[PDB]
Image (tube, rainbow, N blue to C red):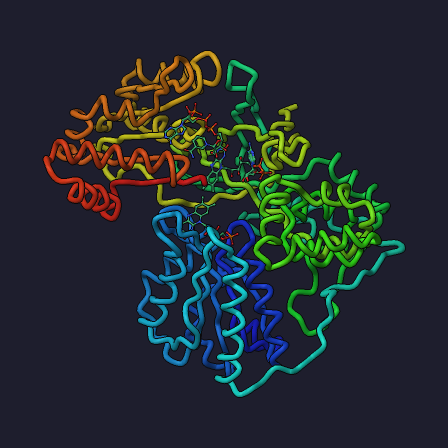
Length: 607
Ligand SMILES: Cc1cc2nc3c(=O)[nH]c(=O)nc-3n(C[C@H](O)[C@H](O)[C@H](O)COP(=O)(O)OP(=O)(O)OC[C@H]3O[C@@H](n4cnc5c(N)ncnc54)[C@H](O)[C@@H]3O)c2cc1C
Ligand SMILES: NC(=O)c1ccc[n+]([C@@H]2O[C@H](COP(=O)([O-])OP(=O)(O)OC[C@H]3O[C@@H](n4cnc5c(N)ncnc54)[C@H](OP(=O)(O)O)[C@@H]3O)[C@@H](O)[C@H]2O)c1
Ligand SMILES: Cc1cc2nc3c(=O)[nH]c(=O)nc-3n(C[C@H](O)[C@H](O)[C@H](O)COP(=O)(O)O)c2cc1C
């Protein structure tokens, strides 16, 4: 259970941990692990949450050992979910890491405020604990071209590492295919994966504790339309976690593993002219690699495409390059290569015709008829299907055995020319209580209510971003009912039209009437020529809010989009503080930002 011991038992001298939430860092970690072999070394990629990083202290036992970290940065600079434990540990510990060699590559995006905060932290932190840095901190930027940044980093990285441990490029040929196909003639039905994420049968034989690798299948006890209109579809779900031993608090997130639209799976099978019901397995050509399979096997093709692979997002340039070899028509083959190019115009065609038009693997297979790749090679080229995160909309103080979700079904007309459907939400919208089971696990956040119940709370969450706040309110109403003394509880919510998508009208009225909700400020962006947003309302309450912040010591919470809405709200607060301090804008910014570091201004960013 010690990654170090895991390394010794398989001759690995290089370990690459991935701090990832949607797979990018995971895949970079996988590619770097594979790389080690091109230099006569051996590595493995691993999820830090499945291990204890304090074990780094033992890494020096393996000669010429290296630990690499591919870390993504999320909301307010916090780490991804699978890296929180490692991150918490790095802050607690003072372990001496002399003898440890590391390298960090961080995934980020310059348009957010805390650019690669997680990557900079691990790199800086590990040096203070005494470990030795052998290659510079890579700073990838998903705003420009992340893959490109990774490549130019990696190309200097291996040479420096090879120069450090005394080896050199083996000069191997390569293999193209990292896996080979093996079809099964019989197979015991209970020896074949049917969608589980980890241990075989782990879905049928629910056995705690339940986490990311061992999700708990909760039954859907409620699923109802929340919006009055029909322009869009907003839903409220309730999953029973009774007997799961799962604990949660208001502000936490619940992640679910969805299933792709079976009609989409079918079509891909037909277009490839394949038997989606063939039970098979994909094995790593290199029998020395730690990644034996691309996903759980054996399994049918149907299962893989349904529960294990991303078939709805835009195909990566690499996929287009590989697929290219399968276009029996020259002009289509040339177009596929151009979209994979590095040329400026070649990178544009891609950005425009694939990424922005939101074309998926099936659309590409239809738009390029001469393209007929064997399904097994296709499955190896596609990325793993990721879990979708939702802000728990209930309080464990009141619903200890039920996790509530507030979500908007995703469905739009892509510029590709067809209608795209969101995976998790479509799958969730079809679950009818009649037992509909959703695989899920909980992920803690730092979006918690004040430590002391007396501290006033100011919530700003337009649209479905109100979700976590229903939790906060339930809990505050409960605290009051327990004879506790609670500070003021204000909610600033917004919607399109009151008769269209106003959420939780009744529940919100009840809380207000009962005094659990002190003020209920609602803005409607489309019910008039003039658009009204939560920040206009905050501006109208400039006196009171400033009082609660400068005197009451209120806590502020904002939920939704960070770079725009959350940005306008922050600006609005800068203005309020500048007027009532009174102080210069410059000084108002330090004051609002001091609140954040001080822990009183929390942001839960969804995008
Ligand atoms: C910490 C966190 C908390 C979250 N909490 C919630 C929550 O409480 N409620 C909720 O509803 N969601 C929440 N989300 C968003 C949520 O995780 C899902 O991404 C969302 O529900 C859609 O998932 P899907 O699988 O249905 O869509 P997918 O199949 O994953 O597709 C989503 C993608 O489609 C694209 N897209 C969407 N609409 C359009 C359009 N009109 N035109 C072009 N492209 C488009 C975008 O690139 C988008 O990323 C949260 C995200 C994070 C990171
Ligand atoms: N970047 C953003 O600021 C932003 C805001 C809302 C939604 N979205 C996206 O759209 C999808 C629908 O989400 P939803 O249903 O929960 O939201 P929604 O239905 O659009 O509701 C959010 C509310 O915020 C308003 N709004 C828009 N830009 C804003 C800003 N900068 N500051 C404050 N309020 C703003 C909206 O008005 P109008 O729509 O009438 O302009 C609306 O009344 C989501 O998947 C999300 O990614 C993005
Ligand atoms: C909700 C959300 C919040 C993000 N917040 C930040 C951030 O604060 N700073 C940053 O540098 N990058 C931020 N990013 C960008 C990601 O770090 C980048 O897209 C990374 O590649 C994702 O990697 P993954 O697939 O391995 O999780 C954010 C992305 C999302 C989706």
